[PDB]
Amino acid sequence: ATYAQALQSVPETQVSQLDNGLRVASEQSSQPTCTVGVWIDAGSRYENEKNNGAGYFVEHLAFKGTKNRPGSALEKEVESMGAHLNAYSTREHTAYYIKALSKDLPKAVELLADIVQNCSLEDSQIEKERDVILQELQENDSSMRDVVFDYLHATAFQGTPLAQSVEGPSENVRKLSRADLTEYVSQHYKAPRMVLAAAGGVEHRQLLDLAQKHFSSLSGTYVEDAVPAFTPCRFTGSEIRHRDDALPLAHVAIAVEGPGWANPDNVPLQVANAIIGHYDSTYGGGTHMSSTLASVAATRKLCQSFQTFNICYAETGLLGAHFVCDNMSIDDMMFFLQGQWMRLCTSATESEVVRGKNILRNALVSHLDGTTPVCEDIGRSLLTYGRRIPLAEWESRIAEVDASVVREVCSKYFYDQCPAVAGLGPIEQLPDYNRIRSGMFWLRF
Amino acid sequence: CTFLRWASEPEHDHRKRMGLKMLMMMGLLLPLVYAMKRHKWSVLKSRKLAYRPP
Image (spheres, rainbow over the protein chains, first blue to last red):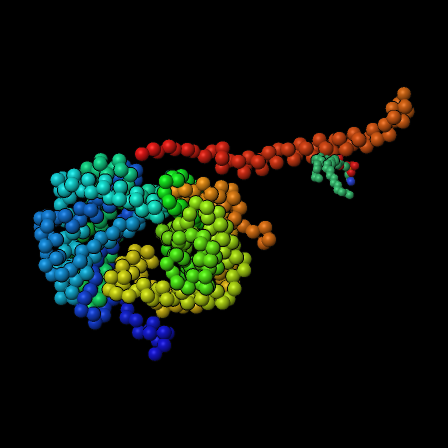
């Protein structure tokens, strides 16, 4: 049995639609558990400065009660069958999913149709969630990576809705009335924006027939005519430096404008990112790692950690690198990161592309282990691609990358481009923006 | 007196032709190098500072 023949035997994702436009998608297995959820085309990029934070607030209030399950009846019902009710919001998506036994799918879908459609949004629970969201803001400030990536978004997408954080500034959380939160759900929690995904021991026909008795009153109509529309987000080469020498380590995120989701350049770029890879000081192979930046950082103790990232949105993205290091090593970290970028742009070699493609295949297959990653894969894929891209198609797209492809795409996105830079902490030795900008081309080239 | 000015300065005409060429080259180079300096320096000249003490 060959990896190629295992990809073909990976089961199919059935997709069926309701009249309201709700899209129902499921990957069946023989597992005795399942993960069913609702993925909505919602996030803070659809929020303006007035209501920024409303989606995170609605997520906060989602499980706190509905018109039929008063406030903790929902929690007792989910708990008494051993299920797990999670939620998450990003700048572009919002998910509500349950991990249940396969026999509990009818109750799991009935729980989500109630939650996504009939949140009481009670005036008394909004005040209680204010203090939590305010406290969670302070808990968030303590995470330097979250701060530095919010900073990267704020400077990269300045002037646009994508600069906003999901949570919103701690000025709107105290002002979001019930009417705001009611309006956010009335504008964004619609069937044509919603995907009902399942994965595990779930038959598609039965999930369909549950959706068309629980979600079938989820309209896609907008008050009078006021349907919200898409707004593209300008990228800005820019810098945001938050200098705080009391913090023991510096966090540096640097990104160029990357492709949106449906751009095939994503596959060659992810490959190339696998060439730079990622490092942590607790790794192992260390100085013998194939990634040049990893081996230099391990040999010289240049950093505590570094990662490559490709964050995608509908029409743009952030393609770059985040590293944590001490105040006297930022310069070397930036030098070697930009040198590796330039070396991929100009002189990627076939063997490192083979290893990078190997890494990408392994990351894609290992990621999809379990019902919950598959359920999120289905929901997010229908929101971003309008379909589920099979692992066979991912393999076919990876098989087409070579060193020439990597050189051309890394040239297009990295070479002689202006990056957004976020620095937090003891960042006095983080290079000046002209010096970082000069690191995006080579004079030898 | 014309001949004596030439005898004192046989480079008079060539010096003035070189001066014209220098003036045109400077009237190109000084604005463009000034633009170069301001391109590099715009990062400093437009940056904004915010103080957020605890």
